[PDB]
Image (cartoon, grey):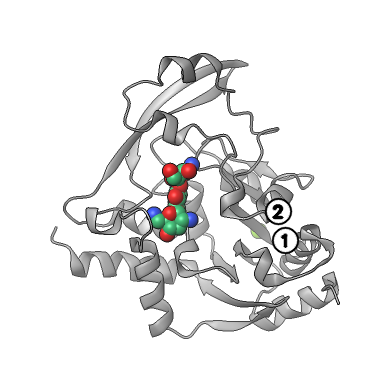
Amino acid sequence: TPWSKSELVRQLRDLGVRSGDMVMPHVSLRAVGPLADGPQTLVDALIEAVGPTGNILAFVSWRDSPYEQTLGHDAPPAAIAQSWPAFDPDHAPAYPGFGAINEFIRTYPGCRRSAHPDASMAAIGPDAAWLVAPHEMGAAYGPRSPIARFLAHAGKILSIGAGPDAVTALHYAEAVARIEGKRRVTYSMPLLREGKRVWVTTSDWDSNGILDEYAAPDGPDAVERIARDYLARTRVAQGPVGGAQSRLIDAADIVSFGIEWLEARHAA
Ligand SMILES: NC[C@H]1O[C@H](O[C@H]2[C@H](O)[C@@H](O[C@H]3O[C@H](CO)[C@@H](O)[C@H](N)[C@H]3O)[C@H](N)C[C@@H]2N)[C@H](N)C[C@@H]1O
Ligand SMILES: [Mg+2]
């Protein structure tokens, strides 16, 4: 029997989501199982659970981000540069690999979208505009990003069947960790500025592993290692949402733990 919105809302309440909360979801729709009206049922349930004063923030990215195609170059390669679509926050689809729910979130009426094409974040609620801007190239997940503001806004990370690798906020810990050997990447994104496409090349922390030992293609990366340790060490509300084992994590606490975890293991 497909899960109804009301059932999901009651499950979210049982897990500890309260009216007014600031929630960042990471969802495995396969784990959740069939929904009465598809993924929108869970989006609607999340919005109802946080209520009209609550907020949702999601890391949605962009289906067509030219990350791999520009990585490591000081400028976009010529063929990429000529024909790639500029990122248009109103129309650019979300990246499927971070969750199929994200396209439903980003298309929800009133959703706001951040300007960073690769790190794009979507937000719903009264504080959405404050969450999503600024979001500048060179500030993907660290200071001055939407994640930074989420962490200052009592954020909760709602993992619905997602693994420990899924915790985007822990890229903030990587950004600020006082450790030697941190990896950086250079890439280029096509932005709209006053209606025109402008290529911007930037560097930022490597979000595929902050040190060499965390940068294997298949992992585990530092986010996964930190989150697994944290979850083995901390009381965290656990329970079902749909068919999915879910957890509700204090974001500031896990990020503080992650900064300490990295700094304990790696010389300054
Ligand atoms: N390195 C291992 C991890 O790789 C992925 O996550 C990571 C993604 O690969 C990162 O994505 C970035 O790198 C990928 C891969 O090149 C690009 O497709 C993407 N546009 C770009 O944003 C994203 N910015 C952060 C995320 N933690 C897996 N989802 C989880 C895994 O633990
Ligand atoms: Mg408020």
| Inter-mark Cα distance, 2 to 1 | 7 Å
Q: Nearer the viewer, residue 157 or 41?
A: 41
Q: Nearer the viewer, residue 149 or 34?
A: 34
Assess whether mark 1 and mark 2 are in contact (beta carbons under 8 angstroms). Answer: yes
Image quadrant where one finds the N terminus: bottom right
Residue 190's label in the rendered image is none
In this rendering, the count of numbered labels is 2
Give whichever of discs 2 and 1 has the lower sequence position. Answer: 1
Extreme residue in the left direction? 267
- Please tell me whether mark 2 or mark 1 is closer to you in this view: 2
Q: Nearer the viewer, residue 10 or 80?
A: 80
Amino acid type at image mark 2: Gly
Relative to 187, does residue 240 appear above or below in the rendering? below
Relative to 91, does residue 217 appear above or below in the rendering? below
Secondary structure of the residue carrying tag 1 is: loop
Residue 214: image location, x then y, percent = 29, 58
* Residue with the mark numbered 2: 125
Q: Horizontally, is 260 left or right of 14 in the view? A: left
Amino acid type at image mark 1: Thr
Ligand 2 within 8 Å of the CB at mark 2: yes
